Image 1 (cartoon, rainbow, N blue to C red):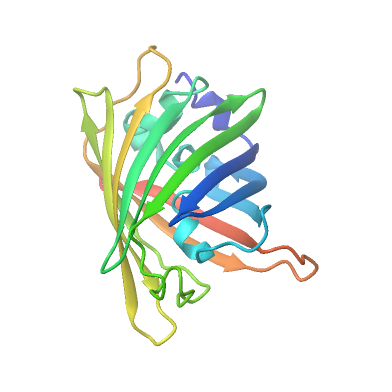
Image 2: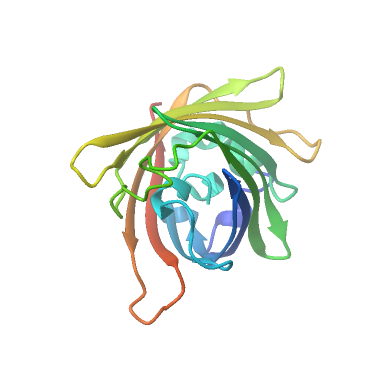
Length: 225
C-alpha cells in the first residue's frame, strides 16, 4: 500500500496535546513506539503543565489507530495506513453521560520516521464535582470494540464506540465517542467495508517518575470480516 510498508516494523511515536477542560488548561507529551505487526503500542505520557485536571483514563482514546493490526485478509479495509505518510485528521466528540463533553481535533502523520499525533482538546459543561473534574475514575481500562464505516462523501470514515470508565464506587462512567477521520493528502485512500477494531489496554505507573504521568501498553486488532 501507500503506507502499509511504513508500519512493517517498529515505529517511534510522539504525541502532543493541548487541552482546556472548563477553563483548566494543560499540556500532555507522550513518547513510545508502535509495532503494527502485533497491533502493539507502548507509550509514556507526561502532564508537562503540572497536575492533570482530568483523569488520565479519559484521555486514552484521544492520546494512532494506524498501529492496529489488520489481518492479511482485511488489508484493503485499513484506511489509517493508506493515508500515510501524509496522514489524517481525526475529530471526535466524546459525550460523558450526565456530564460534559470533549471535542478533539488532531492530525497524525509522519515527521521523518516518527509517527506524530498532534491534538487540540476542548472540554465544556463538566460538573465541578463530577466523576471527571472530581477525579472519581479508577486508574484502569476496559477492552472495547470500535465500529468503523466508510464515509465516501468525505472520502474517509465515521467511527463509533462506547468507552466505559470504572468509577471508584464500583459504578460506571459512559463515554460516547463519535469520530471522523479524513486524509490530509489527496492521494487515494482505502474506504473500508464495515468492520471493527478490538482493543485492550493496561495502564501502569513508572516507579521513578515524579511528574503526573501514564504508562500505556495496548493491543488492537481488526476484525468482523
